[PDB]
Image (cartoon, grey):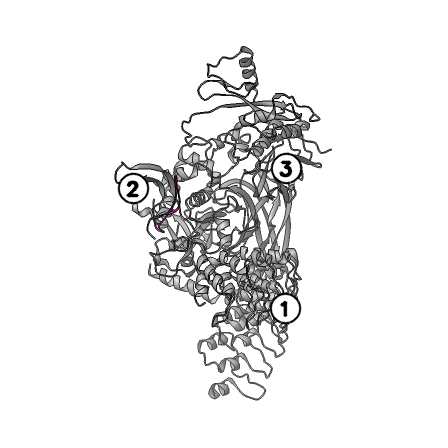
């Protein structure tokens, strides 16, 4: 019975045949609690699967985890096991501990044919797990392109959200896949859709440094100008994360370094908070006013003084920001330099 | 485990003997001999022994069943061609389970004279890759330089893999010209599916085939916007086919089982696991470095001039090795396995691997433009393209803009000069300016060849500064659609009526319309039918009747030829079931 | 009406079907059958008439085989054989396992070369699929007589 599962693993027909000729127990639990049918679904041994299904092997026999054998068979991707388990009877609409449907596990691994068969057999396409993610969102995570095409062709509501409002464009830009971004763009989407933070997918692309997604989004026509709920811009996100080629492309394609947030901060102010040097040189090369005032009228020398970075100053002194300049409180770059 | 035989069932005039086999044995034509103590040894027959991906203890073993049924038992495959922006499937027939494939393959194998190393699939795969690349270098003829449109209907039609195998071994059929040299991968896949090694045929668009060991490619362009001269040691091809085979690597350190790429070299072949290409370990096999250079390398572009001095130009970066695709399992749709070859661009991990491989190799603009062009262009039609120009300077500037269009073969070989256009513009006040221009086929200078792809280049020369901006795009040519109407299920030994519809979208009337239907297990060999003239406004609609015979899953293909174009192929699947008792 | 096309033969693609496997040498055993009809019920069936193991051995009306003897023909037979084989239909390397598939492919190839009219396909397919008796059943049948087919099937 710790060896009945070994007989299931090796598809030992005669041994299990004797074991069920003598014993009347068709299902026992291991220390984990998985039935012999669960381990039969894994290694795809189906002669013993027929032998079990001939007697008592409840397809809907959930332990405390609730993991059906159909869930594992859809997980590893065995087609004939799905057809057999569905022919003998199966409740498709079930939940795990995390309320995962069989379509959820099918979409995550990438098996497109199991998804076709299941959606043919009446599994609801629209669904919401514990968070609320649809199967299209999860399949868009694992970079499974043709599964996205299949879910769109049978039935899909594209602009679906979850508890944190996430369009599939948002997860596509967060996980760096431009291929599914193309399909979601040309079939149907909105670049203007904003998350709970108020972020465009362009903001996420500026954060996680994917470039090809940024190019596709801007060729579609997502606006360069955009206001986060904090008050930021994608130029500000790219400056704060330290990605140079994103800054290069965004500044080539038409941008303004002179932009103000809810606290008046240029990307020079937004850059000297971390001190990426080359982005600072590149922003200074184009038209940006280094002589500037922050919310408390801190010069970028004031924000640079707390870093302790030496050569960042000389580049700022190249455009001769005066040390005469001081904040509202009267503090000067010498004052903050001695404070820090 | 070792060779064994049991006498299970016994009759007064009969024995039923069950021969069993060891997991590691040499494949080939065997012969059984029976030797009693008294008589001379007696010949009992002949058989053949192959690999089985169904056995657990054998090396080449596949766990999932549907993967086996798709990659080993199937015969009706697809090969993807075209540019990476629009992918066109082409129906292909491997036909590995014909009668003569096994003996021909074994006769090709037996020229090795190292017998005992046939028990392992690694040696067989390497040897067969080397031999098939040598045969391709032997029997492939270059293209006829003279133009023969009347015989272009015969030069570039393909029927499958087995006729090409026969023509390569014996040379008693039609040759294969350089226009289609990419068949080789499919042929190798055929041989492996014959022998028991699962295999499939992948297509890499925009691959760097050429010289390797250097992560940089140079390209030279004319003042007018074309490519002065022909050829280069390393160029970016439009597409390239390769072969993947599934096996386990015992000779390597642990952790490399699975898919492997078969790579012949200019002859000794070898195979490399895909995870080695992803991780980037160069020193594991001498071929890993060139294949990893073949996927992600970047190009720089040079500008030739009248004086002979070459100039670097600032252009938009183009990607290399994108949209890796192959045939999906259990269906008739494409799937991309491109996540198995590269990390997502711009991750920490891909930056790490690039820095590591570069460290290992170390031991050994006031204005710009950008271009919008469609992904597909209709035959005998037209389209629109747009070039934008943005300047960053307080002063006005004069600029000269040139546009070039030319057809190219699939291996970067230039084919014909088609069109060029030069104009002068004056940008002012740091304002962007967009220029939209049409592209009509009637304005062209020549008719394009049978299999080409157009390369559209744009070069903006600043009048003051010699540093100029550049952009290039690739466009595939699309042909009118061929509709096939046919029911999904049919009964065995019953008539079945298919319908074929074609619309003349082209501006010319078609003459000598000749179509042909064929298919494995549906119609015996090949059928031909003739038609009247088709005017550019009207359509054509035709009907055929046949009868399925072999139960299961089949598909049929239709093929249309006329004076405007040749070898327009399409396909459609069907499931036929046994009749009710 | 949906206009059906005409046939067209082109041997540009024939050489892609020439196999290279040596078939070898094999002995033959020839059997001849023809359409007849038994007397008890007006039912047509195929009946054997002679065999060619070594010599032609014919089957009498009583159902008993006679003596082997040499094979002599008639001139009209050879003339019509040459004429009908000059314009005959060949099917080489057919991939079949049952007689119904061979019959269907042969009928389709007949229709392709305009040998017979399309409205006769049903009658010939019904004809070629009747049961094939053997020498043991003749005395059970009580005798058979020639039976030519008709459009109505009677």
Circle 2: element type: loop
Image coords of residue B189 (percent x, y): 45, 45
Image coords of residue C131 (percent x, y): 59, 30
Residue closest to the far left: B38
| Residue wearing tag 3 | B494
Q: CA distance from mark 1 to mark 2?
A: 63 Å
The image quadrant of residue B28 is top left
Q: Is residue A6 visible?
A: yes
Q: CA distance from mark 3 to mark 1?
A: 48 Å
Name the chain letter of the residue that bears numbered label 2: B
Compared with B142, A275 (above or below) is below
Image coords of residue B338 (percent x, y): 50, 56
Left or right, B94 with respect to C138, comes to left
Residue located 64% across and 34% down the image: B545
User: Could you classify mark 1 by the number of other residues whose Cα lies within 10 Å: few (under 14), some (14-19), or many (20 or more)?
Assistant: some
Identify the mark at residue B113; answer none if there is no mark: 2
Identify the mark at residue A41; answer none if there is no mark: none
Residue closest to the far top: C75
The part of the chain drawn in magenta is B8-26
| Residue wearing tag 1 | A128
């Amino acid at each position: 019975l710790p060896a009945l599962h070994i007989a299931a693993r090796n598809d030992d027909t005669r041994t299990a045949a004797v074991l069920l000729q003598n014993d009347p127990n068709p299902d026992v639990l291991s220390k984990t609690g998985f039935t012999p049918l669960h381990i039969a679904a894994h290694y795809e041994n189906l002669n013993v699967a027929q032998l079990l299904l001939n007697r008592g092997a409840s397809v809907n026999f959930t332990p405390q985890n609730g993991i059906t054998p159909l869930h594992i068979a859809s997980r590893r991707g065995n087609v004939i096991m799905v057809r057999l388990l569905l022919d003998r009877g199966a409740q498709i609409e079930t939940k795990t501990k995390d309320e995962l449907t069989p379509l959820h596990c099918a979409a995550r691994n990438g098996h497109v044919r199991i998804s076709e068969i299941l959606l043919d057999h009446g599994a609801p396409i629209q669904a919401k797990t514990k968070n609320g993610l649809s199967p299209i969102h999860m399949a868009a995570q694992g970079d499974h392109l043709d599964c996205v095409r299949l879910l769109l062709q049978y039935d899909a509501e594209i602009d679906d959200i979850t508890l944190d409002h996430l369009t599939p464009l948002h997860v596509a830009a967060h996980c760096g896949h431009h291929r599914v971004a193309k399909v979601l763009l040309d079939k149907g989407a909105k670049p203007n859709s904003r998350a709970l933070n108020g972020f465009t997918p362009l903001h996420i692309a500026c954060k996680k440094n994917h470039v090809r997604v940024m190019e596709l989004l801007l060729k579609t026509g997502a606006s360069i100008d955009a206001v986060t709920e904090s008050g930021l811009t994608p130029l500000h996100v790219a400056s704060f994360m330290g990605h140079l080629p994103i800054v290069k492309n965004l500044l080539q394609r038409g941008a303004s370094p002179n932009v103000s947030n809810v606290k008046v901060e240029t990307p020079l102010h937004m850059a000297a908070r971390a001190g990426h040097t080359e982005v600072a040189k590149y922003l200074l090369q184009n038209k940006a006013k280094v002589n500037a005032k922050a919310k408390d009228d801190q010069t970028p020398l004031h924000c640079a003084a707390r870093i302790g970075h030496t050569n960042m100053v000389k580049l700022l002194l190249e455009n001769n920001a005066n040390p005469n300049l001081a904040t509202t409180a009267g503090h000067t770059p010498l004052h903050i330099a001695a404070r820090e | 485990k070792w060779w064994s035989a049991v006498v299970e069932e016994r009759d007064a005039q009969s024995w039923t003997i069950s021969v069993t086999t060891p997991a590691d044995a040499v494949i080939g034509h065997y012969s059984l001999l029976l030797q009693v103590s008294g008589r001379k040894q007696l010949l009992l027959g002949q058989f053949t022994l192959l690999f089985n991906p169904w056995n657990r203890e054998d090396a080449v073993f596949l766990k999932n069943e549907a993967q086996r049924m798709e990659y080993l038992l199937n015969q009706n495959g697809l090969i993807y061609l075209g540019t990476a922006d629009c992918i066109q499937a082409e129906s292909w027939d491997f036909g590995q389970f014909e009668g003569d494939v096994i003996d021909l393959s074994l006769r090709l194998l037996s020229k090795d004279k190292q017998v005992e190393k046939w028990s392992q699939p690694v040696h067989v795969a390497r040897v067969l890759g080397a031999l098939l690349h040598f045969l391709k270098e032997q029997r492939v003829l270059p293209t006829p330089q003279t133009q023969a449109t009347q015989e272009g209907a015969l030069l570039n039609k393909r029927r499958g893999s087995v006729p090409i195998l026969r023509q390569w071994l014996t040379g008693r059929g039609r040759p294969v010209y350089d226009g289609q040299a990419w068949v080789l991968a499919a042929v190798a896949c055929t041989v492996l599916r014959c022998l028991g090694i699962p295999a499939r045929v992948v297509t890499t668009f925009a691959s760097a085939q050429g010289t390797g060991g250097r992560l940089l490619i140079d390209e030279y362009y004319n003042e007018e916007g074309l490519q002065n001269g022909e050829g280069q040691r390393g160029r970016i091809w439009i597409f390239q086919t390769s072969t993947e085979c599934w096996m386990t690597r015992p000779a390597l350190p642990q952790g490399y089982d699975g898919w492997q790429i078969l790579h012949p070299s200019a002859g000794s072949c070898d195979l490399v696991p895909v995870r080695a290409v992803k991780e980037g370990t160069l020193g594991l096999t001498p071929a890993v470095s060139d294949l990893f250079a073949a996927i992600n390398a970047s190009c720089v572009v040079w500008k030739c001039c009248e004086d002979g001095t070459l100039e670097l130009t600032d252009s938009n970066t183009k990607y290399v090795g994108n949209n890796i695709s192959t045939k999906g399992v259990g269906s008739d749709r494409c799937e991309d396995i491109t996540q198995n070859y590269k990390y997502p661009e711009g991750s920490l991990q891909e930056k790490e691997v690039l820095e590591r491989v570069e460290k290992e190799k170390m031991e050994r603009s006031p204005l710009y433009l950008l271009l919008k062009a469609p992904s597909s262009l209709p035959l005998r039609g037209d389209a629109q393209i747009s070039v934008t120009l943005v300047n960053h300077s307080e002063q006005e500037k004069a600029v000269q803009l040139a546009i070039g269009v030319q057809a190219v073969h699939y291996n970067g070989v230039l084919a014909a000069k088609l069109w060029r256009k030069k104009l002068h513009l004056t940008l002012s006040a740091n304002l962007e300016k967009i220029i939209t221009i049409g592209l009509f086929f009637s304005n062209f200078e020549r008719n394009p060849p049978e299999n080409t792809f157009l390369r559209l280049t744009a070069m903006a020369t600043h009048s003051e500064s010699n540093l100029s901006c550049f952009a290039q795009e690739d466009i595939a040519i699309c042909r009118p659609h061929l509709a096939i109407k046919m029911p999904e299920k049919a009964e065995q030994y019953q008539p079945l009526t298919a319908s074929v519809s074609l619309q003349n979208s082209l501006d010319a009337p078609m003459e000598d319309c000749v179509i042909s239907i064929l298919g494995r297990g549906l119609i015996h060999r090949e059928r031909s039918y003739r038609f009247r003239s088709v005017w550019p406004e009207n359509t054509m609609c035709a009907k055929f009747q046949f009868t399925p015979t072999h139960v299961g899953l089949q598909r049929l293909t239709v093929e249309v030829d006329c004076n405007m174009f040749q070898n327009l192929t399409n396909y459609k699947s069907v499931t036929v079931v046994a009749p009710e008792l | 009406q949906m206009e059906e096309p005409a046939a067209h033969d082109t041997e540009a693609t024939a050489t892609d079907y020439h196999t290279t496997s040596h078939p070898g040498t094999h002995k033959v055993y020839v059997e001849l059958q023809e359409l007849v009809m038994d007397e008890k019920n007006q039912e047509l069936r195929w009946m054997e008439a002679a065999r060619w193991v070594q010599l032609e051995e014919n089957l009498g009306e009583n159902g008993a085989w006679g003596r082997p003897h040499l094979s002599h023909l008639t001139f009209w037979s050879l003339l019509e054989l040459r004429r009908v084989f000059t314009k005959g239909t060949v099917l080489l390397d057919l991939q079949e396992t049952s007689l119904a598939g061979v019959a269907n492919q042969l009928l389709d190839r007949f229709i392709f070369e305009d040998q017979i009219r399309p409205q006769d396909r049903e009658e010939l397919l019904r004809a070629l699929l009747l049961k094939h008796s053997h020498a043991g059943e003749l005395e059970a049948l009580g005798g058979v007589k020639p039976a030519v087919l008709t459009r109505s099937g009677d």
